[PDB]
Length: 66
RNA sequence: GUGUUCAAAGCAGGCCCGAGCCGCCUGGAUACCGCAGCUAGGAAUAAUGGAAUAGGACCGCGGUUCUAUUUUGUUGGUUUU
Image (cartoon, rainbow, N blue to C red; front, side, top):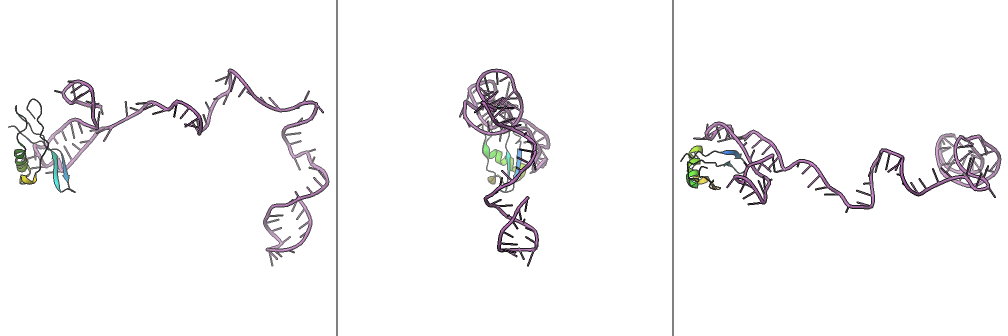
């Protein structure tokens, strides 16, 4: 809910042939909607079939929210 | 520098764009160096120098003499400055 992947510091990694960015998602009261959702959500942002979108990170911010 | 939610701390960090911003962006300072040395300014202070039965400055020079090598095209010879 109210997810909004905020692609901060987007890096067209040309020598690793990829889109490289920081995922920064928002929440009402429950942090960290699941990773493969975020893949599928970052899929439809970029239309890139998200099983090539290999995400990680995803630590839950205190107070839900982000 | 830096909101680690304060803090112990870290070296961080911050954005806009919907997510084509295909990115933009701060940064990660400065302080310390036993000595000995080095460096170069000082020359007080503390030591420190000389002319004494004369020495120091002036090409004062003098006469002697050693020898060093440039030119005499060159070398060789000697000769000198």
